[PDB]
Amino acid sequence: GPMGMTLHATRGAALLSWVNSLHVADPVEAVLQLQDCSIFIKIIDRIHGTEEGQQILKQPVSERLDFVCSFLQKNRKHPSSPECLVSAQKVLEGSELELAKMTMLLLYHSTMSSKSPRDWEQFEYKIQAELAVILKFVLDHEDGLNLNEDLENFLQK
Ligand SMILES: [Cl-]
Image (cartoon, rainbow, N blue to C red; front, side, top):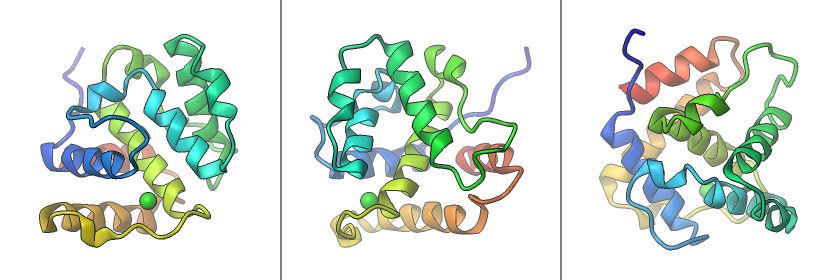
C-alpha cells in the first residue's frame, strides 16, 4: 500500500509529556509504550473517579483496546458519526500515529473532566506551546465531520 501518515516528533513529545505529568505510571519515552492500553485505562479511571479499569487490566491487549475505543466512541460529541475516531487494527499493528490520536482525545476528555485544572506552567515552554496548539485544534475541530482526516493532518505537521 501507499505509505501511511506519520506522527511529528513535537506532537508526540508534548503528548508524552502530558501523559507523564498525570503520574498514573512510571515514565514513558515513546508513544509505542502506550500500545498495551494500561496507561489509557488508568487515564479513563482518573476521568471517571471509578475503578472499572482495574477489572479490564486483567484482559488481553485487544480487549483493553476495545474498552478504550468504546470509551472514546461513547464520549464523542456526535456518537452517531459513521467514521470511528480510532482504528483498533492500526493500534495492534503498532501505529504510533493512531496511539497519538488516542492520547490527544484522552487529553480532551481529561480537560473536560471534574479534575482540577492542570498546572500548564509545569512544562518546558516548548511543550506548553505545543499543548496550546493541540488544545486549540480540539477547540476548533473536535465537533466536525472530517475530524479523522483533520486530526491526522494535524499530527503529521
Ligand atoms: Cl489534563
